[PDB]
Image (cartoon, rainbow, N blue to C red):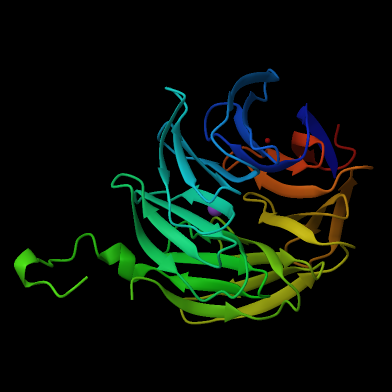
Length: 321
Ligand code: NA
């Protein structure tokens, strides 16, 4: 395959990137604490947001509302409005670096995970933490909501990938439960479902396929593992072998039978979904890769590395959507 580079931002080290769903924009999160907003079609810096002390890693747009969320070294989960360019509020509760933060696709929730070994779910309309998911025994490097089921997947330096059942939390809103405040005691929602144990080093990333019942995980063992599941069980399918340093990030191509991964070995690698064979490698001479993302609808990719960010399309080699 070949990379058709649409945009590059040259900068100090970048840690995260987020596509806007409809505008030709990316947010970037930088090790220096700044968040950049770029129009990648024209190559224009639209805005820069300074709301963090120290590195920012988590960054994501809301899928339909004019908001984004950010998190990093200063422990706070910040909610911004990009139209008013305001930092609206900060959600506090994490006790260490926030690695990932995202919005749910339907419920008014933010998911965050942290070096404090927890995952938190927040209600961004009430501005309260509604669940703390404990059990990992080292940094939680990644967490993601499942796109259609009441599940979360998380990855940790404790060498495990966890799938959590959050159906109890979802059902709480509409339950016919009433409370007389004068009769309360002095003052379940999330349970771990699978503890996937296959990695023998720390795990840096995990991803759900947007439509198929598949999970990818990757980490310090240099491996990308593919898992499949039903409502009642999961299984390890295969491993993509070849990276020669820590794997930072991995994802599914939504519309082709391909897996992508990115690594401190200075490569982005494409693999066949059905056979796990190597399809194509792309390299940078001087830059480790920290993150990759795919646009949900367009076949457009972005990567964060030691010297900035790139936005690109992937095409079959020698082919001159
Ligand atoms: Na996702």
